[PDB]
Length: 50
Length: 49
Length: 50
Image (tube, each protein chain N blue to C red):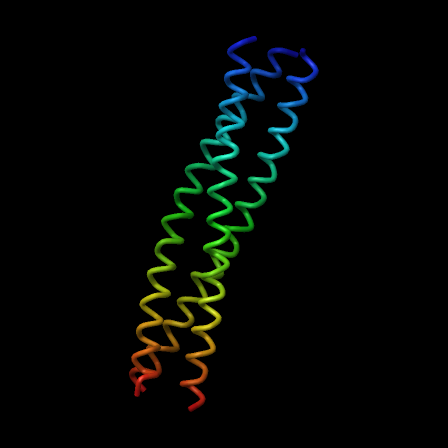
């Protein structure tokens, strides 16, 4: 009984580490999309006014 | 022993909910990137005209 | 070994709560980027219509 409790916990820990990695990648990409939107906003405002 | 099985089942259920939310976040982020690149191409067309 | 299991379970629950809070912040920012993209599309369309 002790062994397969330890097995399930090890599996959960592994999924948790994968979740943290996926979140870190999501944060980096979301950071680039926000910056990209700001760059587009500057170009369209330039087109509107000039 | 019983309180551990309950906690493991609860954790597993929480992990699945997080995986599902992450999958939707990834789906939406892919479409936002795709949309941002399309807008970039449209603004460049106006700039070059 | 049982105490190790209890600690790891508690560690996982706490990390899961931190992940949920981070996901909640990610959703808010993602909601803001979608709104910003829609506003940019209308502005680009406004110039294109000329």
